[PDB]
Every structure is written in C-alpha cells, then in structure tokens.
Length: 68
Length: 117
Image 1 (cartoon, each protein chain N blue to C red):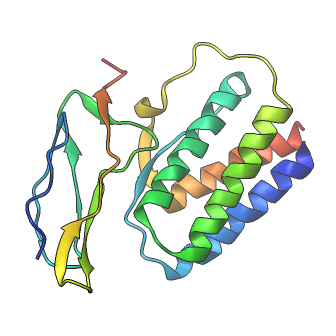
Image 2 (image 1 turned 60 degrees about the horizontal axis):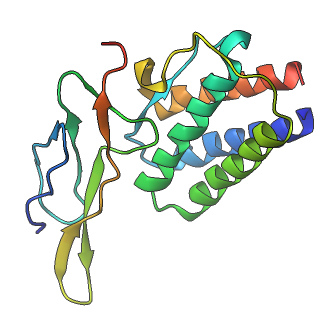
C-alpha cells in the first residue's frame, strides 16, 4: 500500500484507496483554482523490484480564483 | 497556416478514436464560447491543458499524439504570429468539461483557425 500523500499548498485530499493502481485527486481549497496545465492526480504505483509502492509526483498548483 | 492546422485537427480526431478504448477521468478547462477577438488566448488554453493528459496517462500512442499536436500548434502560433489580445478571460475561469467535450470544442476552434487561415 501507499503511504500518506504529500500536502499541496491551498489544496486538500481525502484518499479513498491506498492500494496499488489507485487514482486519487487533490481538491483546491475554496477561493483557489487548479492552474491550467497542472494536474490534481496522483496514482499509487508499485516498484516491483522492491515491493514498495509510492504516489506519483503531483504537478498540481492551486492559484487564486481569477474570478475573485 | 491552414495546412498546419489541418494536421493538428487530424491528430485531435485520432485522439478521439484512441480514447474510445481508454478510461479517461480527466476534466479540463473548456472554452466552447471562443471568439475571434480572443481566439489565440483560447487556443493557448486548449494547448496548455493538454499537458495535463501527458501527466495523467502513460498510454504510448496517446502521449506521442498529444505531444505531436503541441509541437505543431506551438510552432504555428510561433511562426505565423499576430497581434496581442485584451479583455480575454484567464483559463482558470472557464468551466471544466470531460475530455471528450474538451476535444470536441478543441476541434471546433482549430476548424475556425483553418477557415480563416
């Protein structure tokens, strides 16, 4: 299983599944928006070589909602 | 320029076919109400959002194809470049749509570019 995910600034995440192949998504906090080009996704992938799983590195960037 | 936009649209059409056999749970900023006034701004938002697909999926052909779209689209916007636009919305204030709807609008704006190329 994957360890807890890293924290992203101005975002939260509630992981439903920590098992390998699981796909979870961060959610930018109210007042903030996922920057275009960045992803809210992280997937739990296994290192077959060592049997240790880890979350893929997120590219997410939460910026101030331009409409506010 | 229209020749370049033709290749771009053919790639987008290919992606439509490709994702018929790929689970896609990505939602992206989609500007279906794009206008000539802010056409370059809108195109750049479509192009920028593609990088999201590249980050979320490892499917080889899909990756090569979306990357192929970026290379050509950026090259064209770079080569045959024009004015600078104003009074245009930021990408983050567009509504998010399923990848399928994002692609359909992407194909429509590229068609606009072809028609006025």
